[PDB]
Image (tube, rainbow, N blue to C red):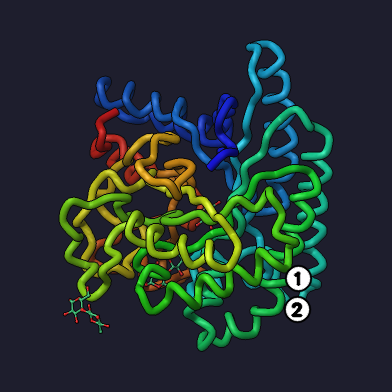
Amino acid sequence: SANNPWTGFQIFLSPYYANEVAAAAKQITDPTLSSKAASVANIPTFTWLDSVAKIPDLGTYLASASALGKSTGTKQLVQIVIYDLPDRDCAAKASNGEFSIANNGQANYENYIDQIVAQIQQFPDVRVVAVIEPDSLANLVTNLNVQKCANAKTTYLASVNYALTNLAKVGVYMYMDAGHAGWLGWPANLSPAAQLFTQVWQNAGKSPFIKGLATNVANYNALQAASPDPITQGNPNYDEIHYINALAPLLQQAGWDATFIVDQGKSGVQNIRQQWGDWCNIKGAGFGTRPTTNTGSQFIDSIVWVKPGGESDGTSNSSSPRYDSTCSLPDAAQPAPEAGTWFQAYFQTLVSAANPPL
Ligand SMILES: OC[C@H]1O[C@@H](O[C@H]2[C@H](O)[C@@H](O)[C@@H](O)O[C@@H]2CO)[C@H](O)[C@@H](O)[C@@H]1O
Ligand SMILES: OC[C@H]1O[C@@H](O[C@H]2[C@H](O)[C@@H](O)[C@H](O)O[C@@H]2CO)[C@H](O)[C@@H](O)[C@@H]1O
Ligand SMILES: OC[C@H]1O[C@@H](O)[C@H](O)[C@@H](O)[C@@H]1O
C-alpha cells in the first residue's frame, strides 16, 4: 500500500554476512565461481540478533549506516531479525538459544529488547526493518500439543508483545514471522493463524509500524511455482503467493491491512525435497530471486533474503544437545555444523546453483 518501508532508502549491506562471504569466496578454488560467490556480499540480507552478543554489532551497523547516508546523500535502512526468545525453537532441537524460561527468561528477553531499543534510539536517521521471532507464532498456531511449546506459550506471547510494543516506540518497521505455505498455508490453518496474528497485533496497539508478516524464513518454498512441488500434495496453497493471497483477506476483515515480505534466499532450486517438512540444510539448494520491491502481489512489500545462505540450519551430529534428526534426513547435507555457524560446502553449492545465476 502507501507506505512500503523500502521506498526511498538504500539498504545497508550486512557487514556480518560480508565478512563470512569474503572469507568463503577466497576458499572457492574455481576463479569464476569465486568471483560469483564474492558478489553475494553486495546482495542485501537480514542480520540476526540471535544472542545478546550481537547487540553491540547492531550499534555498529546503525552508526555505519548513519554515516554512509550522510556521505552518499541517502537515507539508509538496516535489516535485522529479532531471534532470542526464551525456550527458543520449541518444536525442534537445532536452534535452542541462550535464554530459558526458568533462568529469568522473560525478564532477560525484555531487557534484550531494551538494549536493542537503546541502540536504535541513538540513530533516528536510520530506518530499521525487523523480522520478529521466526517460528515462534507459527508454533503457537499448530504445535500447542508440543509440551515445550505449550509451556512456553505465555512467555512467547508476552515476549513478542514486548518486542512489538517497544520497538514501535523507536519507529522500527516490523514483520512478524508467519511460517510458510507448508506450515500455516494449509487452508485449515489460515483462520487459526489469522486469529492469533490479529490478537498479537491488537495487543501491541495496532501500531502502524507493525506492517504485517514474513514468510518462508529459512525455508525453501517458491514464491510462485508454475507447477506445484510434488511435496505439496493435499495443500492447494503450494507456494508462498497462494498462502499470502489466502491469508491476507482474513487479516483485512479483522481490521489489519497487513503486507508481507517473503524470503527467497534459498529458493532458487525447487523440487529437491523428499517431504515438505524437511527444513534442514537441504542439499542442492541455490540462491533464489534477488531482493526486490517488484513482487507481483498487492500484499507483498518485498522479496527478501532473511536467512543468510551458508549459515547452517542445524548440526547433523547426534552427540550434540542440539541434534535434530531432520538434519540427518536423505535430503540434508551431511556432515553439517551447529545452527548459525558457517557451512562452507553448502555456501559454495548455493552459489553454483543460484537461480537466477550470480
Ligand atoms: O521453516 C523453518 C522452520 O521449520 C520448522 O518446522 C516446521 C516445518 O517448516 C513445516 O514444514 C512443518 O513440517 O512443521 C514444522 C513445525 O513442526 C522448524 O521447527 C524450525 O526449526 C525451522 O526454522
Ligand atoms: O481433505 C479435504 C479437502 O480435500 C481437498 O482436495 C484435496 C484432495 O483430497 C487431495 O487428493 C489432493 O491431493 O489435494 C486436494 C487439495 O489440494 C478439497 O479441495 C477440499 O474441498 C477438501 O476440504
Ligand atoms: O543463520 C541465521 C540464524 O539461523 C538459526 O537457525 C540459528 O539458530 C541462528 O544462530 C542464526 O542466527
The answer to whether 31 is drawn above or below residue 73 in the figure is: below
Identify the disc placed on residue 151: none
**Mark 2: which secondary structure?**
loop
Residues at marks 2 and 1, CA–CA distance in whole angstroms: 6 Å
The amino acid on which the numbered mark 2 sits, given as a three-letter code, is Ala
Q: Which residue is mark 2?
A: 102
The answer to whether 275 is drawn above or below residue 245 in the figure is: below
Q: Are marks 2 and 1 in contact (CB under 8 Å)?
A: yes
Residue 100 place in picture, x, y as percent = 70, 72
The answer to whether 40 is drawn above or below residue 111 in the figure is: above
Q: Residues within 10 Å of mark 1 (few under 14, many from 20)?
A: some
Identify the disc placed on residue 105: 1
Residue 56 place in picture, x, y as percent = 75, 40
Compare residues 297 and 86 and report the one nearer the observer.
297
**Mark 1: which secondary structure?**
helix
Identify the residue at image location x=41%, y=44%.
309
Q: Please indicate whether residue 346 sits to the left or right of residue 252 in the image.
A: left
Identify the residue at image location x=18%, y=51%.
226
One can see residue 318 in this view: no
**Quadrant assignment, res 282:** bottom left
One can see residue 70 in this view: yes
Q: Please indicate whether residue 324 sits to the left or right of residue 10 in the image.
A: left
Q: Please indicate whether residue 52 sits to the left or right of residue 136 in the image.
A: right
Residue 146 place in picture, x, y as percent = 52, 85
